[PDB]
Length: 159
Ligand SMILES: NC(=O)c1ccc[n+]([C@@H]2O[C@H](COP(=O)([O-])OP(=O)(O)OC[C@H]3O[C@@H](n4cnc5c(N)ncnc54)[C@H](OP(=O)(O)O)[C@@H]3O)[C@@H](O)[C@H]2O)c1
Ligand SMILES: Nc1nc(=O)c2nc(CNc3ccc(C(=O)N[C@@H](CCC(=O)O)C(=O)O)cc3)cnc2[nH]1
Ligand SMILES: [Mn+2]
Ligand SMILES: [Mn+2]
Ligand SMILES: [Mn+2]
Image (cartoon, rainbow, N blue to C red; front, side, top):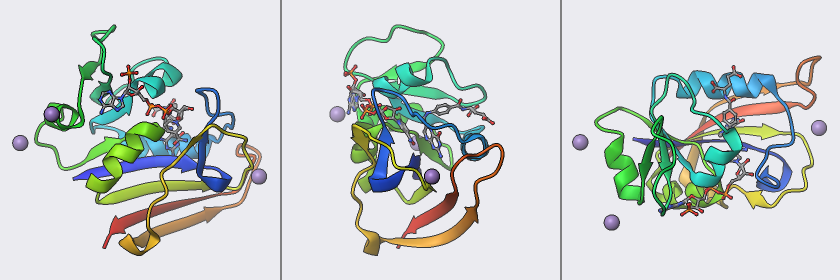
């Protein structure tokens, strides 16, 4: 099974200038809980944005060019990325925009955080078709002293 996990600001913005400008510790904690002990697939730009391997996960990087770091696994196509995960119950795709586009048609589950923040951005989560997806979990949180925007965690499953 393939799942995508992402955090979206208003208008599906996910990034600006190869960064995420907000800081929501509760959402990073949600990301860690839902990805720990699973393989994670990311594009090269997202690898450079994170800047280091994510511990406790098999890190698989898509790039058309040879890898430059043997602490992670480098692959050159979507099918190779999936194969490199082996026989696991759930593969997590962690972006960015170009990678989400390619894996969305293959995904059964979306883990989405909707953040109430207006962000100028240059990268968006793909338009997906709402009729294809059932919301199976949603949890709203108001802003607090640690998290400066309100946010909603949602899990959707392909119908
Ligand atoms: N809010 C969130 O949830 C979230 C999550 C992830 C990322 N982001 C943000 O998203 C932005 C990065 O997204 P992006 O769309 O620019 O880049 P990306 O999807 O992270 O990376 C694209 C790169 O991945 C490689 N690639 C993708 N598909 C491939 C394929 N089929 N075969 C081979 N290589 C492939 C290519 O690398 P080469 O050029 O080396 O061939 C391509 O240039 C940043 O702003 C980041 O902060 C946000
Ligand atoms: N919901 C969601 N939020 C995100 O921030 C997110 N980020 C990415 C890609 N970028 C990043 C950037 C940083 C870390 C990171 O530092 N993660 C630590 C945090 C642990 C914690 O804060 O408790 C990790 O070990 O996962 C992960 C992904 C992909 N999907 C996402 N999905
Ligand atoms: Mn092929
Ligand atoms: Mn197999
Ligand atoms: Mn806000």
